[PDB]
Amino acid sequence: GAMAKAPESATEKVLCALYAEILGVERVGVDDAFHDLGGSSALAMRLIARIREELGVDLPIRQLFSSPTPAGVARALAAKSASWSHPQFEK
Image (cartoon, rainbow, N blue to C red; front, side, top):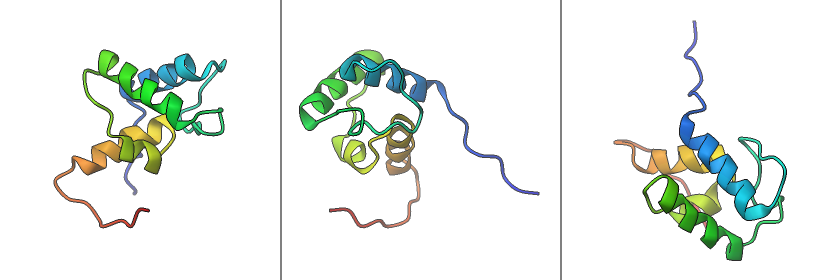
């Protein structure tokens, strides 16, 4: 047997829609790269602002840069809050 994958939770869906509001694109996939959708740091700060209104929390921008996808960032910040983690090099 093997373990099941982590599910796509509600958070990812809100983040996907918030990407669309900020970027002006028709659709956003769960793995859609914010930067390839025309995103810039100037837009990313507006995204973080919206995230506070919707999820009630401040989005850690280091996780946004490390994982510029809506499902990526959700799982990345979650890993930062985990009781254990592997070390990772970042620029």
